[PDB]
Image (spheres, rainbow, N blue to C red):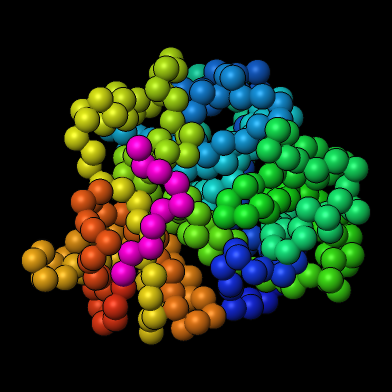
Amino acid sequence: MAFTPFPPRQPTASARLPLTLMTLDDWALATITGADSEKYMQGQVTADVSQMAEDQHLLAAHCDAKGKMWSNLRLFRDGDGFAWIERRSVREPQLTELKKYAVFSKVTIAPDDERVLLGVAGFQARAALANLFSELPSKEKQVVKEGATTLLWFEHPAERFLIVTDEATANMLTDKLRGEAELNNSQQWLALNIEAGFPVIDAANSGQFIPQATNLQALGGISFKKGCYTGQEMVARAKFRGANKRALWLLAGSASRLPEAGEDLELKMGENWRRTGTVLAAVKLEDGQVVVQVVMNNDMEPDSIFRVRDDANTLHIEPLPYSLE
């Protein structure tokens, strides 16, 4: 786009990451302006956009009438409305459905490729950026703005900033960090999301899942006390129904082919069925390992083995770093 992707480098896991400047091509930014921004957005999204502070960002879901997840998104206030970040593969559809019902609202809804999405993660990310900015988001102030730049603070798996900015500023930031930081691309970011249990939704699955199919309730993206949003019945239904459909899973292990988005998984007839889950996202790490993010029944034990339908290797199960209770 406005900004050339950095070439890929084998992604690692959070634990021993050196300073990393990343270019987030596989993500995409969109906005909404107008007098009816709050009103309109509030009814379209699972998160209570009203008590959204000037300094916060959240992972809302966005559903269809039936409570089906069009996509999830990181929302934050921007201008007189909101901006949000989500996977590139889905921006278009989504924005299209979003704009369909904006007909009676004083509201302007657009993609934004003029702005650049960067990631800074790894070893002393905080201290590196601190020489380039007067203020940095923190746990207590999770969104901070400085010139053409908006910084979002993340805590998992280890503390990264997500930077939304100008081409000029990206150039500056890039020229100033090139030397002391590795450059990587989306997959390093993606690996950190997968490592953290944070649902990733690509076009192949927009429409397939209930927010909680995906652990969203666990990550603060559903408001149950709020007024009304498309699909809220279904969503609230699924909470009180008690019966918990499925969930979002972390699978590891070596692999030849990269799992694609929306591909069946295979369980082990040790005492169990066969063709089981669906596939959210995957990254080949250094090892020769992959890490896969999947949606399966909340029912399966520190036992089971799987493998993308058309592949053939020991996939097992790594524990979500957050509690589903």
For residue 36, side relative to residue 236 (left or right):
right
Q: Is residue 207 magenta?
A: no
In this rendering, the answer to whether 233 lies above or below 309 is: above
In this rendering, the answer to whether 35 lies above or below 148 is: above
Q: Position of residue 72 (x, y in %)?
A: 47, 43
In this rendering, the answer to whether 31 lies above or below 165 is: above
Q: Position of residue 272 (x, y in %)?
A: 10, 64
Q: Nearer the viewer, residue 78 or 57?
A: 57
Q: Quadrant of the N terminus?
A: bottom right
Q: Is residue 323 magenta?
A: yes
**Visible residue check, residue 99:** yes
For residue 135, side relative to residue 250 (left or right):
right
Q: Quadrant of the C terminus?
A: top left
Task: Please give the name of the residue rendered at 43% of the width and 69% of the height, measured from the top-left corner.
Answer: 291
**Visible residue check, residue 65:** no
Which SS type dominates the magenta stretch?
loop
Quadrant of the image occupied by residue 18: bottom right
Q: Nearer the viewer, residue 204 or 107?
A: 204
Task: Please give the name of the residue rendered at 48% of the width and 76% of the height, measured from the top-left corner.
Answer: 284
Task: Please give the name of the residue rendered at 48% of the width and 70% of the height, measured from the top-left corner.
Answer: 283
In the image, the segment drawn in magenta is 316-325
Q: Residue furthest top?
A: 227
Q: Position of residue 25 (x, y in %)?
A: 62, 62
For residue 199, side relative to residue 239 (left or right):
right
Counting every numbered tag in the picture gives 0
Task: Please give the name of the residue rendered at 23% of the width and 38% of the height, measured from the top-left corner.
Answer: 244
